[PDB]
Image 1 (cartoon, rainbow over the protein chains, first blue to last red):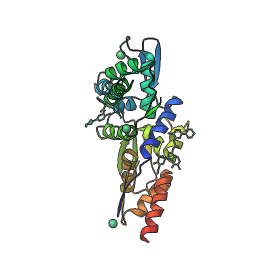
Image 2 (image 1 turned 180 degrees about the vertical axis):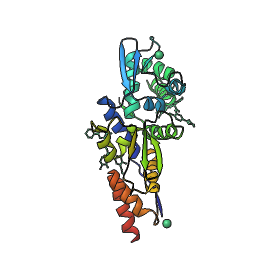
Image 3 (image 1 turned 90 degrees about the vertical axis):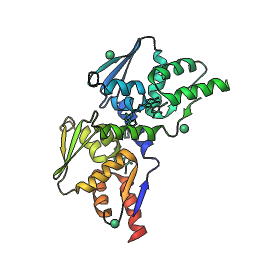
Amino acid sequence: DSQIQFTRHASDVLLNLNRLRSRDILTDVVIVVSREQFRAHKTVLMACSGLFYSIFTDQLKRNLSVINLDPEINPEGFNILLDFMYTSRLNLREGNIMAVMATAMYLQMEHVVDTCRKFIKAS
Amino acid sequence: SQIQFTRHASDVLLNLNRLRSRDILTDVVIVVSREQFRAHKTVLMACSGLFYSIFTDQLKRNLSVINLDPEINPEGFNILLDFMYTSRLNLREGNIMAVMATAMYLQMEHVVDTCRKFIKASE
Ligand SMILES: Cc1cc(-c2cn(CC(=O)Nc3cc(N4CCOCC4)ncc3Cl)c3ncn(C)c(=O)c23)cc(C#N)c1O
Ligand SMILES: Cc1cc(-c2cn(CC(=O)Nc3cc(N4CCOCC4)ncc3Cl)c3ncn(C)c(=O)c23)cc(C#N)c1O
Ligand SMILES: [Cl-]
Ligand SMILES: [Cl-]
Ligand SMILES: [Cl-]
């Protein structure tokens, strides 16, 4: 009898999900943020964001193919967070930290927000 | 910077499992002899050579129901489906052969190799 945990399995799943996203395979929503559109998998968005979890749990919104976010959100900040969702890697820089932080607050992504606070503390 | 979040992928996978448990955004039913299992095509493709082949095939990719070989043990399938969504594999002497054969059919090499390791440790 053995109960085995595969330590790299989740990362490899995420990599494959990102591969699918990159190829537009099984993507089921376009997120619109002012001057940019972004394609994604609803399930991944739900998995990574309190806002998207709330949006797509709502049966009136669950099957929408387009979601318009607040047009005051910085699209670059959104793009950085979308990339993070699919890779575990966060491209934080002095030139984007404030935008990433505010976007992560809006998306309800607490660990990123806290990481931004740590970046600010060390700056 | 590029900050790496070591627990992110695991947390995504567990949230996907929660969505599967609640039947949220599942898009396929897998039939194994008398038994049915709902899942997300994206996760199946991410975890299985067989499902990746099926859902990249022009003729099968838009199917909402996939019938597996009825010779597959549904318990074996359930164990592998749970593994896909959790990274945890329930292996014991009374299920090893069924799990291994199922993993071969599903084209899940790491699980097959782990089964061979279990045989080395126990035969
Ligand atoms: C991996 C990761 C996730 C989040 C992150 C994801 N969600 C949404 C979420 O939990 N969704 C689901 C929850 C559940 N359940 C079932 C019942 O039991 C508990 C909840 N089931 C399915 C789904 Cl899809 C968040 N909601 C709020 N806040 C503050 C967050 O931070 C996150 C943030 C970051 C960051 N940074 C991150 O890396
Ligand atoms: C995490 C995990 C995965 C597998 C596992 C998954 N796939 C399917 C697969 O590769 N899918 C994708 C591949 C690609 N790319 C694009 C760029 O070029 C390279 C291929 N893009 C998107 C997807 Cl979805 C497998 N196919 C064959 N064989 C033998 C396997 O073992 C697996 C098995 C196990 C186990 N056990 C496991 O834990
Ligand atoms: Cl909308
Ligand atoms: Cl971490
Ligand atoms: Cl046993």
